[PDB]
Image: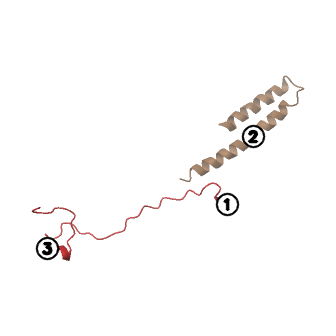
Chain colours: A red, B brown
Amino acid sequence: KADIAIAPLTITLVREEVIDFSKPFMSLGISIMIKKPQKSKPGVFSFLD
Amino acid sequence: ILSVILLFMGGLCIAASEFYKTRHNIILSAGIFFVSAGLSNIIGIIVYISANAG
């Protein structure tokens, strides 16, 4: 259905078995994304907790 | 702001102390206004310090 894929498509063994990939145009790795630290309004009347 | 207003009203009471005197309850009014102004001021300080924790 397409003649070429130009996308952040990762070179993997299972894909290379069925399609051809150019050498890498981008180097990368799996990483962790978290919601940043923020804070913690201690609430009024938290002395009863 | 309410601390400022209460201090102003206490000043008016103390000024009316010398004139229109012999009432003896306007000096008590000035005392109550000044103490209430202090309490308003301390609430304002705590609220300000708490609002700046975020």
Q: Residue at x 73, y 39 (%)?
A: B37
Label 3 sits on residue = A18
Label 2, residues with CA under 10 Å away: few <14, some 14-19, many ≥20: some
Could you say which disc has been placed on residue B36 in the image?
2
Between disc 1 and disc 3, the foreground one is: 3
Q: Amino acid at mark 2?
A: Ser
Residue B44: percent from left, percent from top:
65, 44
The residue tagged with tag 3: helix, strand or loop? loop
Residue B53: percent from left, percent from top:
56, 53
Report how far apart the C-alphas of labels 1 and 2 lie in the structure.
28 Å
- Do the residues marked 1 and 2 share a common chain? no
Q: Nearer the viewer, residue A18 or A40?
A: A18
Whether residue B22 is situated above or below residue B2 in the rendered picture? above
Whether residue B13 is situated above or below residue A27 in the rendered picture? above
Q: Earlier in the sequence, mark 1 or mark 3?
A: 3
Q: Amino acid at mark 3?
A: Val
